[PDB]
Image (cartoon, rainbow, N blue to C red; front, side, top):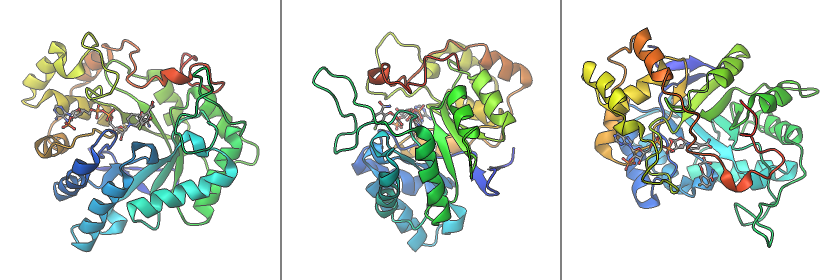
Length: 316
Ligand SMILES: NC(=O)c1ccc[n+]([C@@H]2O[C@H](COP(=O)([O-])OP(=O)(O)OC[C@H]3O[C@@H](n4cnc5c(N)ncnc54)[C@H](OP(=O)(O)O)[C@@H]3O)[C@@H](O)[C@H]2O)c1
Ligand SMILES: NC(=O)c1ccc(F)cc1OCC(=O)O
């Protein structure tokens, strides 16, 4: 298991990164410091997570301390839905750069295919409670992303939560200049994504798996929901390998040639989650984990099901 995967821009991306959604701002600085101290070289960020400044403090300290060189880090962020308008994309990227205290991102993603009305609110609502869309075509948003590469703000651009038809739309864009390097999508044993993953990989697009542990801290969790970390079948595979269930859940996407970004703010777990380069799941283990698919989503963007570009009506 090599530690990085080659992207279609010629750069190498670490296959394990630290997630930061829900990481409290008073804890995420230490989380990122610990992560870098124990070997992480890839941090997954987003403006909408509201903690990029605090992530940046950690990155900057570790650069200043010479624990890691900038060229060795792979920092990812994402353009929020309210910045799809072509004239807003650069400023959104620049704000993220300023908060993260960087002069470039390694990868910048369109966070969701759904554009929203610009403004202070991340989910602008009409008086009846529906999200208010933007009329900016995603192809125009993509062109604006391409400009970021050409201005040196980002090394690579990509997409997130795009279904296969939406990926195809980008790939078929008239005058396409840079292909998406990555599609970041939810992926774990309850949402295995075989169809979308094969499609992306066949086009040379690297897939990053988010919520690999099933996001037990997701805000809308219900007590009766399925639980990957508590699934006795997954626990059994872990016990066989003398690893934790989380470690199996992280190793699983790695062996599918995916990048994976487990989130933690707990120092012991941050370290545990990185200790996944010392064992191998068998083909049987892999197919067994795949068999647990139930098409269950942590992130269904339920408030936007009426949005024209809602990604999850299509089969994949
Ligand atoms: N592109 C998108 O739309 C999108 C959507 C969702 C997520 N993401 C990205 O993917 C990252 C990961 O997804 P996620 O945050 O939804 O959930 P996740 O990584 O599947 O799970 C995070 C949860 O698992 C716990 N945890 C972590 N390691 C553990 C371990 N070894 N043992 C037991 N529990 C453990 C964490 O607790 P503690 O933190 O308390 O230790 C936290 O409650 C996000 O943070 C974000 O960076 C992207
Ligand atoms: N998708 C959401 O509803 C969401 C909203 C705000 C936020 F900070 C995170 C979120 O989910 C995770 C994501 O979209 O990366």
